[PDB]
Amino acid sequence: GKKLLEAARAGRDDEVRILMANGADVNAADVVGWTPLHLAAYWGHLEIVEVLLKNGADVNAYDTLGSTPLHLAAHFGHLEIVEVLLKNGADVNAKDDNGITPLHLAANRGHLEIVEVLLKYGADVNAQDKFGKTAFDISINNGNEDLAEILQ
Amino acid sequence: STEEFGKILLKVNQDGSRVLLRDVAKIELGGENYDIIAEFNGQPASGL
Amino acid sequence: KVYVMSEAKYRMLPDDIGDWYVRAADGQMVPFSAFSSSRWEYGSPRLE
């Protein structure tokens, strides 16, 4: 499991398969609750995200602050990983302990394509975080007009 | 970035309205000072 | 030197953050959880 977490982060595709063929826990979690999926999502390892999912990795694993791999992918602008995660049933409206959704994160960093995909799978535009802010609110505050109209 | 500086929150109005820095200022990268301007054969230049 | 700091057991866990209170202008004690949000990310422990 520990070897897998590491290999997942290092984007070592073959290594991930090997430990998989030797049956390491797909849902192994480090000290902050990140799974190999969290790791591959954050660092942008598309092929490892796909191998992990087809080996039954929990697509909706959450860390110790309630954040899923979909949060990480959306936030860091990994459009393909977002789609792969969504196509594998990732909860598009997943909230972390802050009430923050993947749409909030994508909106906030202005990842327009990602925003569109999220909406495409039925992201709730009206979803508010702990401060009552929506993605729309965020687009306005950031003065992102392109993003702002897409959210209306 | 100028975007981050522009959304600096100066105050919230009693009607919950927001006054951002960009609402009272122009925000841009620009010289620490504007006193020195150089040309190389009449064309805009810098130098050391 | 004189040093102020949290006793160890109150600065060990992420959840400990919301046990610290600040006093508002009107005298009210407000927990960190009411004006902040947090997330895990990666960073460098040694920048060269």
Image: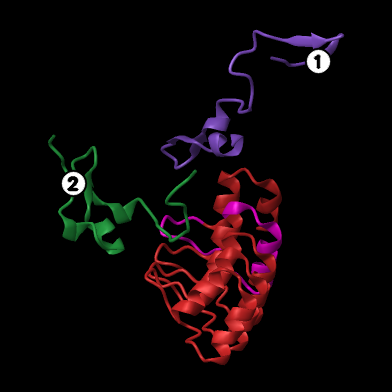
Chain colours: A red, B purple, C green
Span highlighted in magenta in the image = A108-133
Circle 1 packing at 10 Å, graded few (<14), some (14-19), many (20+), is: few
Which residue is at the front of the view, A5 or C39? A5
Residue C14, image x, y percentages: 31, 62
Q: Quadrant of residue A40?
A: bottom right
Is A102 drawn above or below residue A36 in the view shown?
Answer: above
Is A57 drawn above or below residue A138 in the view shown?
Answer: below
Q: From the image, tell me which residue sits under label 2.
A: C5
Mark 1 belongs to which subunit?
Answer: B
Tally the marks: 2
Whether residue A125 is visible: no
The quarter of the image holding the C terminus of chain A is: bottom right
Which residue does the image show at 67% across and 53% down from the upper left? Answer: A147
Whether residue B24 is visible: yes
Q: Is residue C41 magenta?
A: no
Residue type highlighted by circle 2: Met
Instruction: Determine the secondary structure under disc 2.
Output: loop
Residue A76, image x, y percentages: 59, 59
Instruction: Determine the secondary structure under disc 1.
Output: strand
Q: From the image, tell me which residue sits under label 1.
A: B44
Specify whether A85 is left or right of A98.
right
**In the rendered image, residues at marks 2 and 1 fall on the same chain:** no
